Image 1 (cartoon, one colour):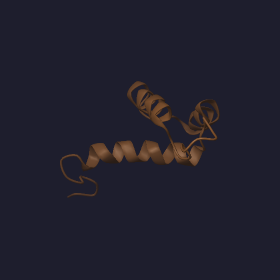
Image 2 (cartoon, helix red, strand yellow; image 1 turned 90 degrees about the vertical axis):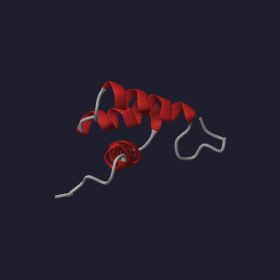
Image 3 (spheres, one colour; image 1 turned 60 degrees about the vertical axis):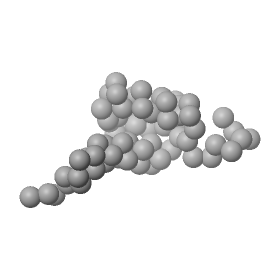
Image 4 (spheres, rainbow, N blue to C red; image 1 turned 45 degrees about the vertical axis):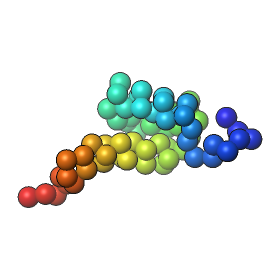
Length: 68
């Protein structure tokens, strides 16, 4: 969608991204770009979203990153 106030992401776009994250954990090097073309985003914006969603699960019950 364009000529609307949906510059970065949308309800539809996040829906397919969430669906994808559930289905396939992470898209590979070619496939993330395949999605970015297909759905319509940049491979960077895609990767950032895909980072944010795994990060959310990490932060959920403390930020267990390099926690040792």
